[PDB]
Image (cartoon, rainbow, N blue to C red):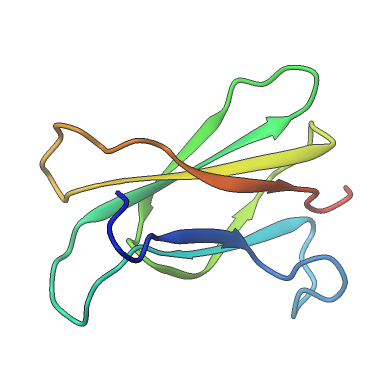
Length: 109
């Protein structure tokens, strides 16, 4: 949610060498809170192709905190958008509000 120190989600430095060489791939990364304690909740990622129209696609099996998310198969819009949502492990009841992520231009092809 939104306590003292709020969570943040951004993309990764991709474009030039992106470390290795993939056939068009992106890289994300985010972190909720976790004050050095246990707790194994769960989180999902969201990414839609920002263009004339869009249907928004989702992702699951995501770790509360990712070190270098790796997505691939993005080709349809000129710019892509990405947000983030979270919840507990198996307690479906609120899912909190969709936190705002960011928008940028991924691989060119």
